[PDB]
Image: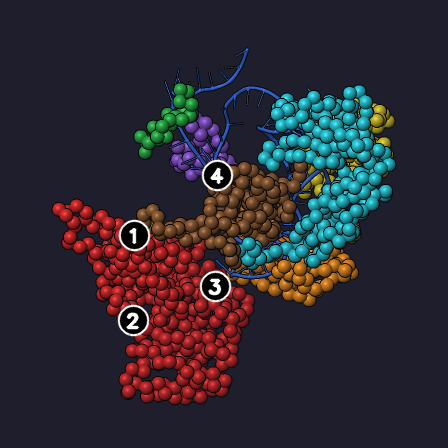
Amino acid sequence: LIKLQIQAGQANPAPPVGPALGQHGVNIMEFCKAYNAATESQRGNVIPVEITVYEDRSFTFALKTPPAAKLLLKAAGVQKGSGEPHKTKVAKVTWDQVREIAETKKADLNANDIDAAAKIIAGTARSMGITVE
Amino acid sequence: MRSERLRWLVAAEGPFASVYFDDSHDTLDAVERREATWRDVRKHLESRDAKQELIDSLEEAVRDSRPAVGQRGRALIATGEQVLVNEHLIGPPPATVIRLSDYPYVVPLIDLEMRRPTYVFAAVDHTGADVKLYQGATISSTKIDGVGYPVHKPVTAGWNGYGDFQHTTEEAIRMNCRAVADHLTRLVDAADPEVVFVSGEVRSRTDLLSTLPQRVAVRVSQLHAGPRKSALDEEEIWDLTSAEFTRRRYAEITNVAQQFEAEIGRGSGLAAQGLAEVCAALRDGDVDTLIVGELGEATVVTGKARTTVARDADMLSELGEPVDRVARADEALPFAAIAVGAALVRDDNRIAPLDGVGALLRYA
Amino acid sequence: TANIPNKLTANVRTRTGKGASRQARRDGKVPAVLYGHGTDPQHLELNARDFAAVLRSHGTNAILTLDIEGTEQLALTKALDVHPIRRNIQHADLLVVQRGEKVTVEVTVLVEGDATPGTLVTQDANTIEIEAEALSIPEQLTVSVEGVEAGTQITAGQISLPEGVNLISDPELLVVNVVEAPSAEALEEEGA
Amino acid sequence: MAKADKATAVADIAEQFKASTATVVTEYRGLTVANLAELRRALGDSATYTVAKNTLVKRAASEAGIEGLDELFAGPTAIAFVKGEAVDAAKAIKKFAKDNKALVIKGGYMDGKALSVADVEKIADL
Amino acid sequence: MLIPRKVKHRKQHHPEQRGIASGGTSVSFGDYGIQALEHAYITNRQIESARIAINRHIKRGGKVWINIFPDRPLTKKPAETRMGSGKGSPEWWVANVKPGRVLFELSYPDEKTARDALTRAIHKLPIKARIVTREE
Amino acid sequence: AKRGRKKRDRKHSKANHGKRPNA
Amino acid sequence: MKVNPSVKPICDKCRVIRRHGRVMVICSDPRHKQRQG
RNA sequence: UGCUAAGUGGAAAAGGAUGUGCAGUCGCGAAGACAACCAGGAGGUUGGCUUAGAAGCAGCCACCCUUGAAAGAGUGCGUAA
């Protein structure tokens, strides 16, 4: 069972996918057409997926929410995080816009309540120099 | 050639003017050729509808250079808002080359380049020595002096041979040799030269070579020059070392040939030839060394990005992205090779690669 | 602060000098002097193992209760003579005190906490002078450095003291000087 | 663990049994954290699946009338506090244990008397 | 390398190497220090090698103090000459060290790196030494 | 330097008491 | 084998033992095998 | 009355080192300490930057939160990654 992060708007590119599952016996042509069709709802956000394989060299995959680090970048408008966090802070984020990432990530978080789940996203914030009001 | 000096050339964007020509202000019927070539390139740029900024950025680069001695070529590469590449060449190109396109043309620079690595030139006699270190633009000079003054053994010894200047002169010469060896070892440890030319005589050049450690004694080329009182000029030193540097640069091509042949024979997958999979490997970023053959008029169709390239749009459509432009192979492939920080090697008609291109990879 | 004094046994020195103090230290005792306001010097001897035991758990300014030939006396540790190499206790000056008497005592300060990550905490003054009654000397005064950033000075005037404790040292001593963390280009420029 | 921390832990565990109507003892040797987190959500609605030391819990058992349950605290130890109802746990444990096969019940408790493994699952059949 | 800006008398007798240190035997600026255990002359070429070994092991953070300065000069006379006819010119600067004297100091947030950084500097001095702290 | 070392080392006998002539 | 006056446990799997009046370091990795001499 | 296993006694340095004897401090421990065997060692997440590549494990900065019995922005080996 492998993991990979593929942006929604790309199907059958050379770098990310080809060598990735090119050694597990999984057909590459049939997966990309299926993945692209399923992922055509976002079309602008990279969303990961896990290839749950069977011994028969078939693929079955369930899609995931776009990563928390990428999601929090557009909420602030800055294209990249702080090279030296806690000294240079790229932008500002209030407690309001954090909750939407909690809801979008609710299916991929082990937390129980929106209050506890909000602190998980706040942890990623200071790791990349983003202030939480 | 490395991919460091041309790395910032990738960052620059805009139209690129690349001129390779002959700059030999030797004789009186040779200065005229300079402005003849200047007029030729001006009219070519006029015919290709170049922006004025290129021309008014080029005239001063052409006209403000102190003329190089003998027969030397000249290489220029500019964007219009600034100059980027401006050097002399070992030998003038057979044909004046002018190009105006978005991709710079750097193939003639791969071999023809008045730029050799750092090296040391030492003149030694068993009374001292003097050392010059070359790291490109800067030259450093040092004079090693001796502590044993009477390095000459007179015929006289004394009354019936009592007293003798055999050992007390050998020790002085050994002191001088030890001092020179220590200084040269310090220079080798600091600057890491590739060649240490030593010019002296049969006696005080083979005993200093026996004093140096194995670190430096492996990279020593022995010269045959004259006395230290005469002193040497830059032209003489250049002519002395050119013969060795020729063989040294030939050996690298030989070693690359051996690596390519071995990797092709094993069929492991660390070697690629022909555009078909060379372009794929270059796109994948795992190209370690690029060998440029006689590509000539072969064309490549690069997609949306300035880097991604493919042999034809028929197999580029497998990426989904559509074709954006068409460029010449010997003009776009080296660009992507520099982009992934690969080494560039100019074939000497001894590799015979398929389709006039080759690549040593980094993995499967 | 309420302190319970520590009971010790002291024996009057028969002899004095350097030839009799070396014998005392080779045996396991330490010479001592019990002077004070009573205008009454006394040359005593304390067990080396026992005397060092209370100092290990009660600071240098311990409150002793010496038993000199059956009586009980209240004493204070004034000064200690420690060998630079062997780390012994070559002597001990003891001062007689009474309850409710104000004594000028130099106590130690410990800095605790974790300041801004890009900061370096330096302590200048190791100790400060403190006036308190004989049974209420604090064995340690602590200062907290937390959230302190860049150039900041925790001067001796900001150190909190227990009630009933005065301050003899003026509020101008610099105790803790927190500054920016030195870079790698600053370690090379120092000391050359 | 520190001596004081062991004393602190018993105080919380002792009250957890007093406020709970019943309890179920199991073993978890072989359940991945993902497998366990599955049980903390299936049973998390009404039950709590906590574990602790054997002897440390043995002290807490002295505050209540479960003195006969000391046999089941040896080996890997799991205790489930059922604050609400008994049927909710009596059937959710059965299906989860059957799926994983690495979760074997040791016994139970109700009305001051333990109930064996065979008779603790039949409560769900009431 | 440390050299005094000026000294009154440039050729002096050899420093005495007797007794233990009368002062400067405790850590005053940093948190850790190096205490000497025997007499020697510590040249300025070994002080500079000792404080670079400390800097490289701690990389970025911390501060280094040097409590001994090379004031006193030693003179070496020209090589391969007989005895007499004057006195040699000064050649290197030393610092009279006696047992108990604290040479170097360091204040670093943790203990392992700070303690191992001082051990690297001890292996560059011609004496025996030990690591000491501010506690009693 | 074995001869010189041995000759000086024998000043540490019990009958010499740490001294000998010519060191 | 390495023969130096000073022997130390290069890695975390090295052990220091004493055979026949000699200090030795024995490790699974043959490079770290060394003895005192 | 004890010590030495080296023929030390009957030569020598920086330094290396589970040789052994004596005395003194501090931690952990029947609430089970150390060694050993059995099972977990997770989720956000491939933390942010740099990099062709950098995913705990060239390099720089930070070093959070959650489920929890515990799980480090990761102690090593390993892969181009």
Q: Is residue A88 left or right of residue D121?
A: left
Give the vertical position of B153 relative to B235 (above or below): above
Dot 1: chain letter: B
Which color was chain D given?
yellow
| Chain that the image shows in blue | H
Q: Residues within 10 Å of mark 1 (few under 14, many from 20)?
A: some
**Figure chain in cyan:** C
Q: Colour of chain E?
A: brown
Chain identifier for the orange-coloured part of the image: A
Camera-nearest residue between F11 and C161: F11
Q: Which of the labelled discs sits on residue B340, or is there none?
A: 3
Viewer-side label of 3, 1:
1
Q: What hue represents chain F?
A: green
| Chain ID at mark 4 | G
Of residues B64 and B349, which is closer to you in this image?
B64
Question: Tag 1 or tag 2, which sits nearer the N-term?
Answer: 1
Q: Amino acid type of disc 3?
A: Val
